[PDB]
Length: 105
Image (cartoon, rainbow, N blue to C red):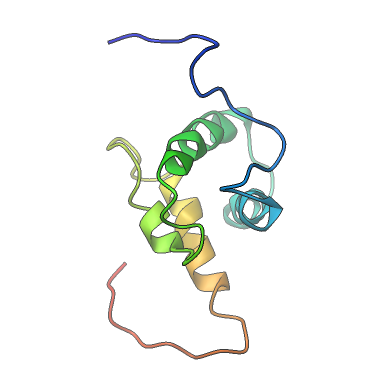
């Protein structure tokens, strides 16, 4: 209940080992898809959340955007979680497989 210091895992501007532009920048784009002119309040929950989503390197190699959309704490119905959903669609635009329809949004 209440915590904040410099020793903690402070946010890094440069692309770390468990996260690069391909992933980071990928989010900045999605956030722009939903709305053209976003706001700080949209990044206050995105950057803060991305920090926790990075703690668990599970969507690095296999890249599971859908999994990142569920990494939310709880109070994230529509604001940051949605952004992760927009990445699940764009992912279906590469020369690999048309995929199937099973998971229900």
